[PDB]
Image 1 (cartoon, rainbow, N blue to C red):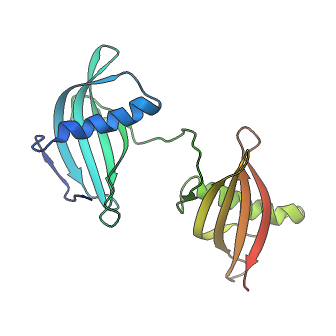
Image 2: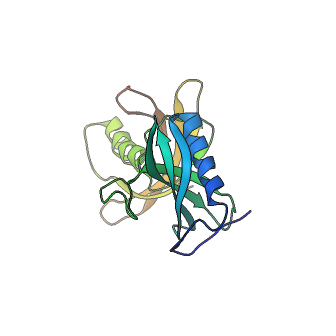
Image 3: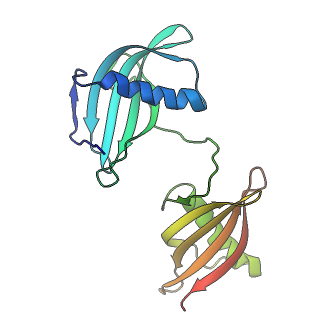
Length: 199
C-alpha cells in the first residue's frame, strides 16, 4: 500500500528504472513485444484523480532507440498502484511536441462491474435508453440523463450489462434498471430486458 502526489520533475532519484520495467512487462506480455529498456530518461510526477506516475526512459524498438513515457494510476484509499499505459515520445519534455494522448481498444473478459460516465458505459446506456423505449415502437422521447452505477457480467457466450440510471421527460426524474448484452460485430448492443426503479 503506497501512493504519491505532487506535480513536479526529478532525475530518477528513486528506483524509477524498475517502475518502467513493470509497465513494459505488462503491455509486452499482453499485446506488445518489441521494447527493450536501455537507459532511464527522467522522472515526473502529477496528481490525477488521486495519483499519477509519469516516467520516461530510453527503450529499444526493433533495434532503434527511442524515449517512451509510462503512466501509472494509483489511489490513496485502495493503495493499489497499477500501470495504465505508455506512449512513444521523442527527445523532449513533452509528447514529441505532437498529439499522443491515450487509447484503449483491446478486448477483455471477466465477471466484474464497470465505471460510470465512461465511453463503454455511456455508450451502452445511451443505446439502451433509446433502444428500450424504441423496443415498444418507433419513438425517441428522452436519452441518458445520469448514470447511477453500471456493472458488466460474462454470460455463457455474450456479456450481460447491469446498470442503473435516471431518465428525464418534461422535467421529471425517475430511475430504472437496464439489462443489455455485449456482442462483437453483431451490430453493437442487444438490449435483453428492462425494469423500473420505484418500488
